[PDB]
């Protein structure tokens, strides 16, 4: 119902805009924006399209055009790093997916990906788990896609949220649970990690 | 000053029910709605219902009429959320939030939601305490620096956290990366622990991951052999 981007990136001092689009945006003038730091509760920073609560930095500002609302952060500062949710109403309170905004504090770094096939022990036990370990990527925002041969695979995928390493890059894991037949039946399986417009793909075949 | 305070985290079996409280303070309890919004990990916030703290009138989301019950206690200024017939997809952080403006406007609950309680984590898992299955991750030099190989252990299906992993009884520490666990839809955790070691030692040095799951009193020393 409400569509907003998963992750956004911007350097300090510059400006950027997060877009939220939905049929409910044009209907009412209730679209709002909520800021959420990790481990804490969301907080309103823009409501009724463009109104700003007292105590909120004046750098935040909102607007809408047609069925697309927009939150604009001018003079980006480090404490703006957070999740920003859009809020509207369509026969009930409804929210977007949330946008992870990262204030770049180091160079964008692509992930290292390590892909393990199922253990022969696990296979002989009538189970199969492909393990895709992702590390050393900044910012902490990736999308993982599993492919059987070339066909995408959505069923059986379990992926963690990124976690901050000691070098302040991020790590994450994705697991593809598989039937032994499914594993032996295909030429290969691939773990595709997209990150900041770049992609890293590792592939394993049952004949290895 | 204006504060909403929720109860602690909960762990429930499927089919059970859970009661989360929300203690208000610093404002006229009966002038503002109390909404309830949950946040499943890696998902968008979802509204489930509000209660008029003055009249006790309620309004739930379509997916919750029948299994949800919101009540209010005027004397303790507390709202309670009762969710029945818990499924595994009910796992989420549950927030309460004050409804902006009040019971005077038609959209007097949908103006702004502020403040929010700190949230209460509810975890629906069919699993009582359970020890892990540990499988070997055979060495692979494909995505490691030159001359080294990555090997590890897959700690599959355990509950609850935590799990600790060492290698060779702690003698091997450099190159160890224990990744945070994933909470699967089954309600069970799984994690991996890998270690980058010299590729020449594979045929000489023994590599054992020492997994310790104290909740289930389970310990596993899994030797990781190379696949010749």
Image: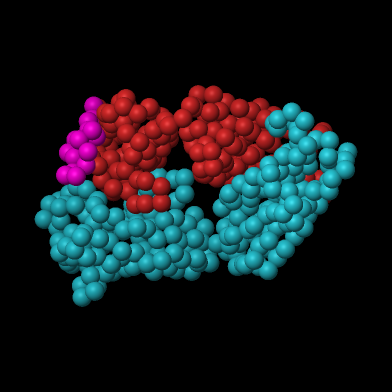
Chain colours: A red, B cyan
| Residue B138 found in image quarter | top right
**Residue A35: image location, x then y, percent:** 32, 43
Q: Residue furthest left?
A: B104
Against A24, is B16 above or below? below
Instruction: Residue at 68%, 69% (x, y): give it.
Output: B217
Give the residues drawn in magenta, as a range. Answer: A49-65
Residue B88 in view (yes/no): yes
Towards the viewer: A169 or B26: A169
Instruction: Residue at 64%, 28% (x, y): give it.
Output: A201
Q: Is residue B40 left or right of residue A68?
A: right
Residue A52 located within the stretch drawn in magenta: yes
Q: Is residue B202 left or right of residue A191?
A: right
Instruction: Residue at 48%, 27% (x, y): give it.
Output: A107
**Residue B207: image location, x then y, percent:** 80, 48
Towards the viewer: A122 or A105: A105
Q: Quadrant of the N terminus of chain A?
A: top left
Q: How many marks?
A: 0
The majority secondary structure of the magenta stretch comes to loop
| Residue A151 found in image quarter | top right
**Residue A11: image location, x then y, percent:** 38, 27
Against A195, is B136 above or below? below
Towards the viewer: A71 or B67: A71
Towards the viewer: B1 or A88: B1
Against B40, is A79 above or below? above
Instruction: Residue at 17%, 49% (x, y): give it.
Output: B107
């Amino acid at each position: 119902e409400l569509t907003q981007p998963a992750s956004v990136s911007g350097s300090p001092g510059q400006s950027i805009t997060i877009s939220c689009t939905g049929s409910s945006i044009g209907s009412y003038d209730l679209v709002s924006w909520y800021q959420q730091y990790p481990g804490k509760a969301p907080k309103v920073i823009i409501f009724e399209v463009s109104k700003r609560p007292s105590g909120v930095s004046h750098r935040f500002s909102g607007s809408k055009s047609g069925n697309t609302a927009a939150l604009t952060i001018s003079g980006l500062q480090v404490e703006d790093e957070a999740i920003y949710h859009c809020y509207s109403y369509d026969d009930m309170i409804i929210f977007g997916g949330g946008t992870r905004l990262t204030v770049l504090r180091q160079p964008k770094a692509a992930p290292s990906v390590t892909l393990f096939p199922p253990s022969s022990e696990e296979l002989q036990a009538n189970k199969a788990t492909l393990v895709c370990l992702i590390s050393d990527f900044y910012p902490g925002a990736v999308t993982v896609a599993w492919k059987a041969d070339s066909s995408p695979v959505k069923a059986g995928v379990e992926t963690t949220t990124p976690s901050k390493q000691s070098n302040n890059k991020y790590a994450a894991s994705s697991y593809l649970s598989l039937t032994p037949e499914q594993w032996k039946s295909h030429r290969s399986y691939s773990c595709q990690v997209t990150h900041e417009g770049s992609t890293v793909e590792k592939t394993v075949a049952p004949t290895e | 000053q204006v504060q909403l305070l929720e109860s602690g985290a909960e762990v429930k079996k499927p089919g059970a029910s859970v009661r989360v409280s929300c203690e208000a303070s610093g404002y006229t309890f009966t002038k503002y709605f109390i909404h309830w919004v949950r946040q499943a990990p890696g998902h968008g916030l979802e509204w489930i219902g509000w209660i008029n703290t003055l009249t006790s009138g309620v309004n739930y989301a379509r997916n919750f009429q029948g299994r949800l019950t919101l009540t209010r206690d005027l004397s303790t200024e507390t709202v309670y959320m009762d969710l029945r017939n818990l499924k595994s997809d009910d796992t989420a952080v549950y927030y309460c939030a004050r409804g902006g403006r009040g019971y005077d406007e038609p959209w007097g609950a949908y103006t702004w939601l502020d403040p929010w309680g700190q949230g209460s984590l509810v975890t629906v898992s069919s699993a009582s305490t359970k020890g892990p299955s540990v499988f070997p991750l055979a060495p692979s030099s494909k995505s490691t620096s030159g001359g080294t190989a990555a090997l590890g252990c897959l700690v599959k299906d355990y509950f609850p956290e935590p799990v600790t992993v060492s290698w060779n009884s702690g003698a091997l520490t450099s190159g160890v990366h224990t990744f945070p666990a994933v909470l699967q839809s089954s309600g069970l955790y799984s994690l991996s622990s890998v270690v980058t070691v010299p590729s020449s030692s594979l045929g000489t040095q023994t590599y054992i991951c020492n997994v310790n799951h104290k909740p289930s009193n389970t310990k596993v020393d899994k030797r990781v052999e190379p696949k010749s």
